[PDB]
Image (tube, coloured by chain):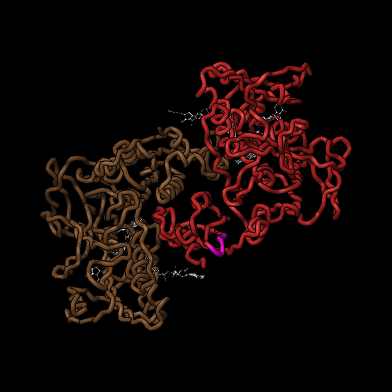
Chain colours: A red, B brown
Amino acid sequence: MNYVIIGGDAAGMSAAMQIVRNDENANVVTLEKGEIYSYAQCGLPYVISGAIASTEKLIARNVKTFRDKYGIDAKVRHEVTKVDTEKKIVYAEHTKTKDVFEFSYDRLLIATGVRPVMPEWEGRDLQGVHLLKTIPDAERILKTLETNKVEDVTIIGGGAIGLEMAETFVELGKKVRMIERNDHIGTIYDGDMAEYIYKEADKHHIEILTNENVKAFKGNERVEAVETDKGTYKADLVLVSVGVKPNTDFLEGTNIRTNHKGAIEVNAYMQTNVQDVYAAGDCATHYHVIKEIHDHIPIGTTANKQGRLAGLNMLDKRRAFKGTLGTGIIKFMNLTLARTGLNEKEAKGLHIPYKTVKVDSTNMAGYYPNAKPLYLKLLYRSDTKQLLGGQVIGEEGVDKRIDVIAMALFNKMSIHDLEDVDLSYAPPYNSVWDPIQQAARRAE
Amino acid sequence: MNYVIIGGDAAGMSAAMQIVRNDENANVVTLEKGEIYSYAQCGLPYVISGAIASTEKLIARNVKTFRDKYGIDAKVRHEVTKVDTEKKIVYAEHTKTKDVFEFSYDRLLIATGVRPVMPEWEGRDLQGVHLLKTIPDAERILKTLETNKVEDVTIIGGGAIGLEMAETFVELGKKVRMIERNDHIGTIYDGDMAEYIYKEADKHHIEILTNENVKAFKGNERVEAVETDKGTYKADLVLVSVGVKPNTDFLEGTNIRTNHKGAIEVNAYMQTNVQDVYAAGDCATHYHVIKEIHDHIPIGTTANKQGRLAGLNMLDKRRAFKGTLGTGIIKFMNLTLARTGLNEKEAKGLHIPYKTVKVDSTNMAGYYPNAKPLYLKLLYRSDTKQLLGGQVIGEEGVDKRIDVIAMALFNKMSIHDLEDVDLSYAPPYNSVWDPIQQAARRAE
Ligand SMILES: Cc1cc2nc3c(=O)[nH]c(=O)nc-3n(C[C@H](O)[C@H](O)[C@H](O)COP(=O)(O)OP(=O)(O)OC[C@H]3O[C@@H](n4cnc5c(N)ncnc54)[C@H](O)[C@@H]3O)c2cc1C
Ligand SMILES: Cc1cc2nc3c(=O)[nH]c(=O)nc-3n(C[C@H](O)[C@H](O)[C@H](O)COP(=O)(O)OP(=O)(O)OC[C@H]3O[C@@H](n4cnc5c(N)ncnc54)[C@H](O)[C@@H]3O)c2cc1C
Ligand SMILES: CC(C)(COP(=O)(O)OP(=O)(O)OC[C@H]1O[C@@H](n2cnc3c(N)ncnc32)[C@H](O)[C@@H]1OP(=O)(O)O)[C@@H](O)C(=O)NCCC(=O)NCCS
Ligand SMILES: CC(C)(COP(=O)(O)OP(=O)(O)OC[C@H]1O[C@@H](n2cnc3c(N)ncnc32)[C@H](O)[C@@H]1OP(=O)(O)O)[C@@H](O)C(=O)NCCC(=O)NCCS
């Protein structure tokens, strides 16, 4: 009956909505550190590029609707600093006044996501050095672009956010450099597939520096350069995108179990090891359908799914989380980059015996106008032929293929079974055998 | 060792290639009535529209390649007129010289497809009255368009071909009318989804006539009008697209079993009831994954799969055909029209208890530029919640959704399990919950 939720975004409010819809007696208090509930972080790079009019467009439901329409007691500017799991009390600080409030719970959900990491580099705090996570973050980047002469941009790190932001700055007419981390090589794409990414970057004049270590950001009051172990380069704006950390520091002393990076362990039902405490989203671990271990792959689709499940389970509407597949998709310049399941680094790290098939193909009938190349790779088990993962790169029809591969991994299909599926074909959409099925046929 | 195949297209040559690849000693004779092997009938409307340079582009493999590279004794202009299943002899008549040849078989495959039906209308034979099946057919339509002054085009019938051809003639700048058969209402799309098709046709000034019966085609040497039971309309070119008949006429007298429309019955292994006689493609029946009965849904994806399977089984590499889902996709003007599994007419005819969910949604994040409307309908069993079928209509991202639905149907998934699949999401491709999942959530 008293439900407390910490975090006011995808996971926390997916949970809140379930409770509110399915328990009319429920007293729901939500605790959010900032001033903005339920917004699409994913739209941030597209507001910065100007493709979306403003950050207000990213708001999915405001705090006024949560309060007035749904009877949720949604707090803004409340940062939780401590949880007492024996007394069942949450302590929150008002972020302006610093006055302390306490909230009694019957069931608690931790839905506090992750934060971007800023390594301990000289110059970290120079004006124009940025992280990107929140609407205020995006506004500070725009403010730097508005109030300065920005021509050279350096991105530290790659991955989804780094690549999307490279595109965003290219589209804003900047000269973009990105300095990539070698600990992140092979983590998303195999090396033979990442080649298409390097080619596309190079084609659009995005300089990618490999095997080079940042050491300081240089400047007086603002950044003007980035220093690495191999040079110093002019930069008028630096975006740091090198990793994330679960926002779980405040739970120190609660006995709530955490993996090595600080993500909260959850069982099938979003429950922690501590009675009546739950977790969901980027702050929690994510059972992996193919690894069969609790991984950490923080994304918004998983966050919404786990938050919804956590709400249902907190109402005792028992329902197991089926897992994540590690699915990810990125728009990068002219290319779409998609992957799901295990890549080679992951399969090797698990000691799962696998083979691969790679096909350079087209997204549709080769004779049809504007058929575009499509590169597709599948991993499958050597013994049982179970499909393990796929990576797809090209300009069109990539999302279709990764979604089909995601479906196959979800159903634990053997690679050769993909040959039997009655997928759609007409000349404007596909070939009579889909690229996935042609790759399946080449498998042993 | 002596394999005889009748039909030199998708099913027949898919079989041929398997036999040739997997039996070094095999003597393969293929018998094709026309002069063209292995071509994409699907590309024909797109050659006619000018989108594809010529019919030559549609040829996948030459008879010269089959003969020289693969050692297949590929005959052209050989029309099989009878089969003696006791003596195991195939009788073919040369289409020009009328000479008769005998071919002895150890295993026989019938891969003779369907033919478009021309009802017995006065004027059937007027110049400018056309069927569309073969490359010569497309050439004759082009000849009519090149010579004759064509302004008004009438299409009799609908379905994929009628719709694709209405677009083709619009793009060639003609005034297009379609006269639709009421025996085919609800057979492909439910009435509520067909509405989008009528709106789209009307939008582009394609006049569609309903509950109106053709009576005659009028003209001198060439066609110039179409008469129905309600009027007579100018037409300089008529395309008739009212149904297909399996090309199995010639088998009368054998004991080879056929369904009511003449399609040859095949078991799991593409075998007829007659020892050592197989069938595949449009001339055969198609086991339906969801109906659990042998249907007839002639389409090129199925023909290639069945032909390949027939070749394999003819070599005793035993492999069962898993079935068809009745998947179909059409480009029509600005819309993509897709369906798979059962629609309401099919579910009702089978007495399967079902419910439906319909969602008016978008293909991607609503705040992202050029997000387009997406209309999606699912049917599911009211008892077990098994997904039964789906129809998807919209401008972009329709093929992706139907392929995901096809995968779900293939795996016999419950509608609510769709909520748990880790499908891809980024703002340019989808919403955080795919439309399929939002519809799934609305189901009982
Ligand atoms: C630039 C960018 C692009 C992205 N693109 C995609 C994409 O294309 N596809 C995709 O699926 N995902 C994408 N994501 C990720 C997706 O946005 C997140 O996974 C999702 O927001 C996670 O939801 P969550 O509720 O777990 O955490 P969050 O959305 O981070 O919400 C956590 C909330 O908790 C609050 N909080 C933290 N600590 C406390 C505390 N002590 N007290 C009170 N409140 C606290 C924070 O203020 C925050 O609002 C992207 C993210 C970024 C930054
Ligand atoms: C305009 C059009 C558009 C299409 N679009 C699509 C689409 O978008 N997607 C899709 O999946 N499918 C599409 N199809 C259907 C697809 O083309 C067919 O399903 C596929 O060609 C069927 O292959 P099949 O080998 O069984 O029959 P066919 O390809 O018809 O081949 C049978 C062959 O047998 C020969 N033959 C017949 N009788 C005899 C005889 N007695 N003796 C000797 N030879 C004989 C014929 O000459 C023919 O070449 C389309 C068809 C048309 C006409
Ligand atoms: C906005 C947010 C609170 C969603 O709240 P929600 O109420 O769960 O979602 P909706 O408002 O779409 O409502 C969904 C429910 O209403 C039901 N519903 C919606 N329309 C319906 C209709 N017309 N008829 C019947 N039922 C309907 C749905 O079936 C669904 O039911 P369920 O929850 O029992 O499965 C949550 O997603 C959020 O905070 N998001 C943050 C933004 C975000 O997603 N960020 C990550 C993006 S990277
Ligand atoms: C063209 C046609 C003969 C295909 O013949 P095919 O030889 O089976 O097809 P391909 O040439 O693509 O060869 C496929 C085989 O080679 C193998 N192969 C292809 N490239 C390979 C490679 N690079 N490395 C290893 N193996 C490869 C495939 O795995 C496949 O093997 P399998 O048959 O054992 O599964 C047949 O589809 C046809 O006649 N089509 C008519 C046109 C049509 O499709 N019409 C209907 C469209 S509507």
**Furthest-left residue in this view:** B122
Q: Is residue A89 visible?
A: yes
**Location of residue B273 with respect to A187 vertically, above or below:** below
Residue A382 belongs to the span the image colors magenta: yes
Q: Position of residue A135 (x, y in %)?
A: 67, 31
The quarter of the rendered structure image containing the N terminus of chain B is bottom left
- On screen, residue A333 versus residue B147, left or right, reads right
Q: Is residue B172 visible?
A: no
Q: Position of residue B202 (x, y in %)?
A: 31, 38
Give residue B200's quadrant in the image: top left
Q: Residue at x 17, y 73 (%)?
A: B81
Q: Nearer the viewer, residue B149 or B85?
A: B85
Q: Residue at x 17, y 52 (%)?
A: B224
**Location of residue B328 with respect to B82 vertically, above or below:** above
**Furthest-right residue in this view:** A220
- On screen, residue B293 versus residue A49, left or right, reads left
The quarter of the rendered structure image containing the C terminus of chain B is top left
Q: Main secondary structure of the magenta part?
A: strand
Magenta-colored span: A379-383
Q: Nearer the viewer, residue B338 or B305?
A: B305
Give residue A119's quadrant in the image: top right
Residue A169 belongs to the span the image colors magenta: no
Give residue B385's quadrant in the image: top left
Q: Nearer the viewer, residue B129 or A178?
A: A178
